[PDB]
Length: 21
Image (cartoon, rainbow, N blue to C red):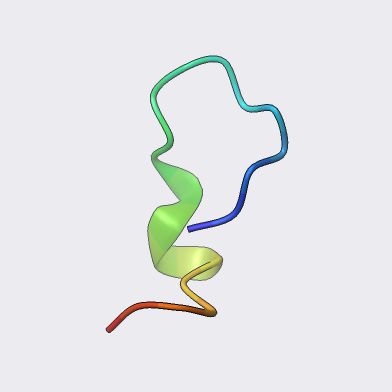
């Protein structure tokens, strides 16, 4: 995921997984 500060559930991970499968 990517920190965006995205209070606070971090659910966009799948679109910002530039570090994860």
